[PDB]
Every structure is written in C-alpha cells, then in structure tokens.
Length: 169
Ligand SMILES: Cc1cc2nc3c(=O)[nH]c(=O)nc-3n(C[C@H](O)[C@H](O)[C@H](O)COP(=O)(O)O)c2cc1C
Image (cartoon, rainbow, N blue to C red; front, side):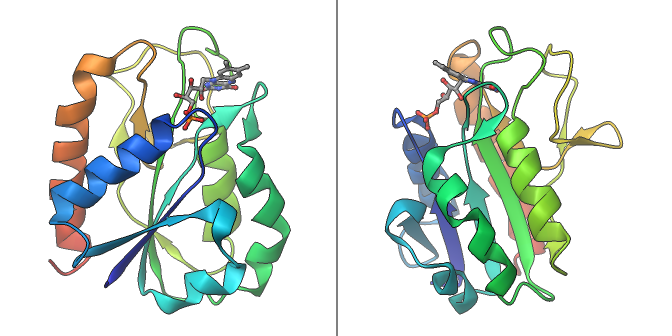
C-alpha cells in the first residue's frame, strides 16, 4: 500500500484505533497495518507516507515495543517523508504526561528530516502537561478511550479526512 501504519500496543486499544484508521482510509489496498513488535526499522523505508501509533505507558514513557526499536530509528531514511502520529492516553489519570509517547516519537522522527503532518487541536481535552504539544497543538491525533470513548469515532473520521489531502488522496 502507499501508506504504512506502524503501531505498538500493550492492552490492545492502539491496535483497535489503527484498524479504524485503516478502515476510514479505504482498507488494505490503501493502508498497510504493521505491528512494530514484528518489524525491523528498515521496514519503515518502504513507504513515502507513514502513520505512527503509540500509547503512553509507565508515566510518560513509550510503549515497550516502540522503546525497543527507538535506537534504530536513526538508520531509517526519513528524509522528505511525510509522517502523521496518533496515540492513546488517559488525560484524567495522567494529566501531567498525557500522550507523552507520541510527543517523544515525533521529536525524534522529525529531527531526522521528515515532515510532520496531521496537527490536532488541544481544546477538546483537559490536561496539564504533554510532550506532544507544540505551539498550542498536538503533533497528532490524541485518542482517550478511558475518558472520552464516545468521541473516538468522529475524531478518527475527521483526522483521516484531513490527512487525505496531505497524502495525495
Ligand atoms: C500503568 C498505566 C500507566 C499509564 N501511563 C500513561 C501516561 O503516562 N500517559 C497517558 O497519557 N496515558 C497513560 N496510560 C493510559 C494508557 O495509555 C491507555 O489506557 C491506553 O488506552 C493504552 O493503550 P494500549 O491498549 O494500546 O496499550 C497509562 C495506563 C496505565 C494503566
């Protein structure tokens, strides 16, 4: 497929979101779903457009599978690639570290010459601090199944619609 979606998940929520994103884009013919747990960093080279999904765990840390491949990101040719991000988090329980993992990945990947695409507004959330916030916006789609599960479907629908422009669709 033209778009490669790489996600990591601990309790399965992020995988469910990844599947919904794939569906909104039009299915398997448009977006490839790849669990980062089973991927080599080089797998990310095969796509010109990437979607990176990662939930935040351990109080402001990356999900373990993303943590494992983090050091190899440096060897990937990210130059000129457009990359979008999404993450699952809990704004009530972790108000000071909401969506930090998504922020950690974007900071690293954007520093390797890629172009971040898919900024999202922070106004629909209530949190104190987040490493995923840049200039009053999230670097990607923030999903909260723990406190706002009823907003998930429309958030994905809206975000994908916005992404289609950026990915030449
Ligand atoms: C022990 C624990 C730590 C967590 N830490 C964070 C955190 O630091 N920041 C955040 O935004 N959410 C945090 N969460 C919420 C999870 O990211 C959230 O439940 C998410 O849906 C899990 O996604 P997954 O099923 O794809 O692994 C944590 C949840 C638990 C139970």
